[PDB]
Image (cartoon, coloured by chain):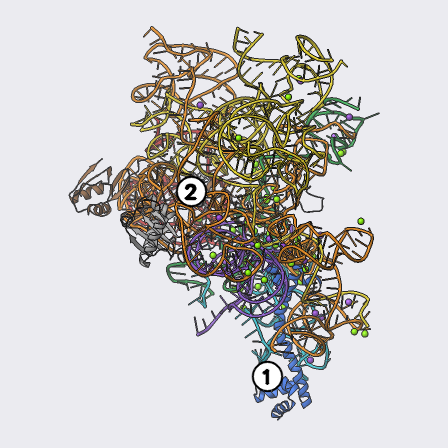
Chain colours: B blue, D brown, E yellow, F orange, G green, H cyan, I purple, J red
Amino acid sequence: RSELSGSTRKLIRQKGSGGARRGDINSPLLSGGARVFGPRPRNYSFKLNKKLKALARRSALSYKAKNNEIIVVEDFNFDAPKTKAFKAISAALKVGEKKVLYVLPEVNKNVYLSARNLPNTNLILANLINTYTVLASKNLVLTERSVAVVNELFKA
Amino acid sequence: PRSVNHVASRAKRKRILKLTRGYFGARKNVWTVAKNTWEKGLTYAYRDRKSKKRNFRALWIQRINAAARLEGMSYSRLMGALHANGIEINRKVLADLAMNHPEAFRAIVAKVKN
Amino acid sequence: PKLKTNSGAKKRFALTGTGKIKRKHAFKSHILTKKTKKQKRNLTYFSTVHKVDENAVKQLLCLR
Amino acid sequence: MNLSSLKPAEGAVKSRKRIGRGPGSGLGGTSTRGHKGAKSRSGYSKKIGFEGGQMPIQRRLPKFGFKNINRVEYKPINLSVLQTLSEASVEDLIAAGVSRNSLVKILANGTVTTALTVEAHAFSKTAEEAIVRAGGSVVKL
RNA sequence: UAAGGGCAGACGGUGGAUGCCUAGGCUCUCGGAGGCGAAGAAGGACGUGAUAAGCUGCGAAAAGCUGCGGGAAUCGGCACAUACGAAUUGAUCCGCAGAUAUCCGAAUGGGGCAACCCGUCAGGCCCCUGACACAUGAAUUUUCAUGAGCGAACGCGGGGAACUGAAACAUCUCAUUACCCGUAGGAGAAGAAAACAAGUGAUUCCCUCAGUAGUGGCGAGCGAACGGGGAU
RNA sequence: ACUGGAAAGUAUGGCCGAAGAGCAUGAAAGCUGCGUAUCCGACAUAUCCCUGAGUAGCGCGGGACACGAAUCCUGUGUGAAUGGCGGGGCCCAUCCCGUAAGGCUAAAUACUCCCGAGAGACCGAUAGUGAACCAGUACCGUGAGGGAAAGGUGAAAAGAACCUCGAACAGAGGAGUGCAAUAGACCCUGAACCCGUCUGCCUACAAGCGGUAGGAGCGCCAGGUGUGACUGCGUGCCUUUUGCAUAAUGAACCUACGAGUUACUGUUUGUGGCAAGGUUAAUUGUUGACAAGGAGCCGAAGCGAAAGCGAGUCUUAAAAGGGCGCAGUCACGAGCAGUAGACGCGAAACCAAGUGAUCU
RNA sequence: AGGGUAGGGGUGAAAGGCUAAUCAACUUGGAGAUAGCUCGUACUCCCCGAAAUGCAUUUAGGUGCAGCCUGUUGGAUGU
RNA sequence: UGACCGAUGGAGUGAGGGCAUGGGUGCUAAGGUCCAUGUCCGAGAGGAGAAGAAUCCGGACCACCGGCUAAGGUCCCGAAA
RNA sequence: AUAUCGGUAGGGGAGCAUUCCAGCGACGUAGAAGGGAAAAGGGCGACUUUUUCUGGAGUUUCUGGAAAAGCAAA
RNA sequence: AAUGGCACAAGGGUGCUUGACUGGGAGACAAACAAGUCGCACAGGUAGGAAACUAGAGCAUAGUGAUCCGGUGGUCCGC
Ligand SMILES: [K+]
Ligand SMILES: [K+]
Ligand SMILES: [K+]
Ligand SMILES: [K+]
Ligand SMILES: [K+]
Ligand SMILES: [K+]
Ligand SMILES: [K+]
Ligand SMILES: [K+]
Ligand SMILES: [K+]
Ligand SMILES: [K+]
Ligand SMILES: [K+]
Ligand SMILES: [Mg+2]
Ligand SMILES: [Mg+2]
Ligand SMILES: [Mg+2]
Ligand SMILES: [Mg+2]
Ligand SMILES: [Mg+2]
Ligand SMILES: [Mg+2]
Ligand SMILES: [Mg+2]
Ligand SMILES: [Mg+2]
Ligand SMILES: [Mg+2]
Ligand SMILES: [Mg+2]
Ligand SMILES: [Mg+2]
Ligand SMILES: [Mg+2]
Ligand SMILES: [Mg+2]
Ligand SMILES: [Mg+2]
Ligand SMILES: [Mg+2]
Ligand SMILES: [Mg+2]
Ligand SMILES: [Mg+2]
Ligand SMILES: [Mg+2]
Ligand SMILES: [Mg+2]
Ligand SMILES: [Mg+2]
Ligand SMILES: [Mg+2]
Ligand SMILES: [Mg+2]
Ligand SMILES: [Mg+2]
Ligand SMILES: [Mg+2]
Ligand SMILES: [Mg+2]
Ligand SMILES: [Mg+2]
Ligand SMILES: [Mg+2]
Ligand SMILES: [Mg+2]
Ligand SMILES: [Mg+2]
Ligand SMILES: [Mg+2]
Ligand SMILES: [Mg+2]
Ligand SMILES: [Mg+2]
Ligand SMILES: [Mg+2]
Ligand SMILES: [Mg+2]
Ligand SMILES: [Mg+2]
Ligand SMILES: [Mg+2]
Ligand SMILES: [Mg+2]
Ligand SMILES: [Mg+2]
Ligand SMILES: [Mg+2]
Ligand SMILES: [Mg+2]
Ligand SMILES: [Mg+2]
Ligand SMILES: [Mg+2]
Ligand SMILES: [Mg+2]
Ligand SMILES: [Mg+2]
Ligand SMILES: [Mg+2]
Ligand SMILES: [Mg+2]
Ligand SMILES: [Mg+2]
Ligand SMILES: [Mg+2]
Ligand SMILES: [Mg+2]
Ligand SMILES: [Mg+2]
Ligand SMILES: [Mg+2]
Ligand code: NA
Ligand code: NA
Ligand code: NA
Ligand code: NA
């Protein structure tokens, strides 16, 4: 009501007109009037304990390992960005039918460029693993050094 | 986000308006008049489901009274004799026999007219 | 904003180990003499807040 | 589970209360407010410490006491805790296993029976006697 | 007998709900920039087209003029248009730089009822015309630069309420708020101890200290600093 | 190849991918168009011995400081010192700290008229800006000022040559276009209130909220459906009240609109993580995510006004004679409270800055 | 015909008359003032279920605390 | 019986009314008024009394075209001599 | 197994629908949403399914998430 | 004042006195809260009395009213 553009003048006198008593034009009862209890800008962030988040990450990884959707491949480099080469790797590993998440230990610009255009593939560093990203994909492909990084960083 | 349930809101009224068919004047199709009429009818229906049993028992008793007075006895005397002789035929069956099977009613009366 | 403590309550009440609220005794008549020397009941011993009057002193001290 | 079959713990979440939305909900009409009076109006709040005009309790009881703006408060550490720390060193006051840059005072709650070399800001007489009986040392600083 | 009427179905009328749609809003993020104006502003008036202009653009050189760079077949703005022309000798269009730019408006030659009336002096045309100059205040020495007015928020300064709360009300609160007025910059203000404290070492901002110390018809309320952790 | 008015759809079968963002194209396109990833490009034009005097201090009246009379300011009247002076919450002494009455100074901080690039578990034409369109327009007012309504043919105007009735397109019936004209200019879809026509059944001896429960006959499409002779029962609804058919309040009707929300701080509880510990805030690194940040906060001892003592402590000369004491923490969801307009609409009034003597 | 006096201010051969159909002015803003008052408060089913008393009150149609309801709990006794 | 008592989360109510009994007041008036003890209406439908908030009988989970009773009734409207 | 199940103020429990989101499954010019008619269903209900006419381009299931989340009277 | 009590008098006389005490409140009454009422035990030292015993004011129930701010007499904390 306080941010509508109409004036604060009383529309009709209080008594004697024969209709309902009225105040200003910005009332929510009038057409084109105020929006009562509408949305306000908000921050939706909330807090979770660090140990709770670590336990959730470990739980997601354990779910993957138990359901047998974790496979380990050797570390590879690309001389040039080649989407066909990355597609060949995925088809050889048999992770082309569904959604797959690759975990890499380093930047690997050429590999990232090769994997950029494929639909059901995602790439993430080992140190940036999170529960949502782990759970979002059907299959999880780790590399030899990624196994070591995950083991040393997210242990206990 | 903004949520307005236009279709559900209208469908709720249209379903009840389907049940107010046959009423008189505005009561059949004008929403606030038709809805008001419909609920009063539902209270009436609740009361009438109870009163229907009373009405049908009264009808059976009147028919049995007529048939017994044809046979030479009153309803109260016939019921007293029936209960003394311990037969468990109820008033609905007795009235149905009285209207449709007079020989069977005569048999019942002759059994207890001793 | 944070809840503000009532100043008079914070000057008149205190907390104990078990969470009970202790307080001083107001006199019936504050003019001693013409009152029996048994006024040590309201003159020597700190009392506690009655359970019925509790939660009001709590809201005064910000539910503490 | 995965993202398509998420489930919270039983009883962890609960639907909120919504009033003024019809008779079937049990919370419509007057919307849990009763009928009339000050408490049924929009914008009513409670005046804290107000009892309808009677002299309030926080005004009819008297003020008492004063607080010390230079008050030294020690941290109570007991002999049983000292034994627990000693059992997996002798020279105590490690404080890294517990306070954080504070003054410590040893009190008598259990027993020692073992020769220690306890150093603390202050001691109790019973604490010093128990240390001496156990055959230990007290350093007060 | 249905004059008429009641109920149902079908098909129509009216009306414009609903569903689907939209660059028209709303809230923000990042990076710039933070003014325009006496070399005449913001905002207007009057004009300007092949055909009346309602918008748009432009200004008596008037949907427009010139140069350089880009580019390659259509173009001559829009409100459902025809005509007539331009254009591969490179139109139209885009980037940068130029030319012209009527009248009012701080308006500044004098007046005035804004977009008008009336002048003086030097020239040139020829009673009438086009082109110059002709205000005021402050540094300044009559030569010279500067200022006036407008305009989002943020800054600083000069004045400064009341409804309201205290369940009345006067101290108190609302609040050094609303509002009026003056005046900067891209930020402003502050800033280098006649300091805090009971050792630190100029300002500013964030998290704590802390709803604590205090203050108060000790009511309603108001409310720090030291210290610690940071940005710099 | 199929369906279709029309493939971008479906089904085969291929190809590109540092390009599978998007928009358009007669339906939904990585391979039709503009684009996108990536790479390249500017003739100009811009941007990057000395040491602060009406001073310090003081009297009177006031103000700002969290502070309603130590510090700082000053209307009025006074007024020094040159190790001295000032401060440490009234006043004196010791101690400690500093060196007034001259000035300048970046960074970290506040904001968006404007320009550019983006985004949204934000709206979708009574919503969202007052304004999607002719919008601060039309209209209203002397004036300051107030202030609307109003989007959608079709893929493509192919926007209906010609004929018939008629004075006339006023309108319609054809023909033609088109997938469709019951898409024909107010044109997508086309609801309700409200207004008609036709068909079926009922109705001119009948009397009250108009229904409800029984129940013949007639009429339609094989156990359903329309109507309904005749019978029983029945004083609407909301609100307000001790109590309302009330002759107490309220509504013409329909469609649309319309009223406990959010933020912070407490407290209780459901569910969780750690556990004698629990937890980070601002912020910082590597790339919203991971890692770091322990400052701080609660817990771990109490009693006493306090000095203080301590599983004791307070009272006492002394006593149990008496009082008080001998698993948490951090979140997520929910209830409640306070502070914010705080469930919504409604005063009479108060204050501030302006507009009006074209009426009187 | 032109001009001047502006809000509790002006003007009044005085009626508290008149001051733009407004007078014990109008416009915008503070502002969503305040209203212990009236009215209104929208989906569903299930379980339980009051009070209209006392004390106090610048209180009497408001409120605080008791009394009476409900949920979860731990002791047990209530009739 | 089961809800009496403790501790805690959430309330609403703080305009009552009729009848019977014991009283005050009034006029041994009032559908009056003020207390006490019960009960019902409030917040309670169903049956009889012609039609009545609280008088008599009786506490509605839903269905049934089954049976027994309560108050009160059995010539017809209207069930049963 | 027995008992219980009238209710205003009010307390407690369990659910339906609406808009958008994530994940997983689907549908659509051989006809989506919307509009009209008919039929069936639900311990119970808020409501949900199916057929047909109109319509001519989008819609929907399950699990979890968030709200501009429901009108008969002002 | 009224009511209840009072003869072993709680009614009336003499003698001696200061218990019209310090430190106190097992337990109860009453009560929305604030307030109110009765009453210890023991220790210190007294009055009366031969002793037992009694004495923490008066036969009992009215004779006042908070907090804040001030005054007076004693006895821990401020800069
Ligand atoms: K500066
Ligand atoms: K394409
Ligand atoms: K169409
Ligand atoms: K269309
Ligand atoms: K229609
Ligand atoms: K009827
Ligand atoms: K009336
Ligand atoms: K005049
Ligand atoms: K009678
Ligand atoms: K009969
Ligand atoms: K005596
Ligand atoms: Mg206003
Ligand atoms: Mg709006
Ligand atoms: Mg809402
Ligand atoms: Mg209505
Ligand atoms: Mg209820
Ligand atoms: Mg209602
Ligand atoms: Mg009400
Ligand atoms: Mg009331
Ligand atoms: Mg109430
Ligand atoms: Mg209000
Ligand atoms: Mg129709
Ligand atoms: Mg020229
Ligand atoms: Mg060129
Ligand atoms: Mg001039
Ligand atoms: Mg007040
Ligand atoms: Mg075909
Ligand atoms: Mg289409
Ligand atoms: Mg609009
Ligand atoms: Mg004509
Ligand atoms: Mg059609
Ligand atoms: Mg149409
Ligand atoms: Mg007759
Ligand atoms: Mg007839
Ligand atoms: Mg009345
Ligand atoms: Mg009645
Ligand atoms: Mg009324
Ligand atoms: Mg009316
Ligand atoms: Mg009425
Ligand atoms: Mg209406
Ligand atoms: Mg007069
Ligand atoms: Mg007038
Ligand atoms: Mg205000
Ligand atoms: Mg208002
Ligand atoms: Mg019950
Ligand atoms: Mg209460
Ligand atoms: Mg009252
Ligand atoms: Mg009362
Ligand atoms: Mg009466
Ligand atoms: Mg009487
Ligand atoms: Mg009531
Ligand atoms: Mg009852
Ligand atoms: Mg009855
Ligand atoms: Mg019988
Ligand atoms: Mg029952
Ligand atoms: Mg019930
Ligand atoms: Mg179809
Ligand atoms: Mg949709
Ligand atoms: Mg869901
Ligand atoms: Mg809504
Ligand atoms: Mg509606
Ligand atoms: Mg007491
Ligand atoms: Na007819
Ligand atoms: Na001039
Ligand atoms: Na006058
Ligand atoms: Na509930």
On the question of residue A79 being in view, the answer is yes
Q: Residue D4 is drawn in which quadrant?
A: bottom left
Mark 1: which amino acid? Asn
Q: How many marks?
A: 2
Subunit under mark 1 = B
Which residue lies under the disc numbered 1?
Answer: B90
Q: Position of residue C36 (x, y in %)?
A: 42, 42
Front of the two marks 1 and 2:
1
Write the residue at 22% across / 35% down: D141
Check disc 2: other Cα within 10 Å, few if <14, some if 14-19, many if 20+.
some
Looking at the image, is J67 positioned above or below residue G14? below
- Residue G18 vs residue E113, the one in the foreground: E113
Residue at which label 2 appears: C25
Q: Residue at x 61, y 72 (%)?
A: B49
Give coordinates of residue B70: x percent, y percent: 69, 89
Amino acid tagged 2: His
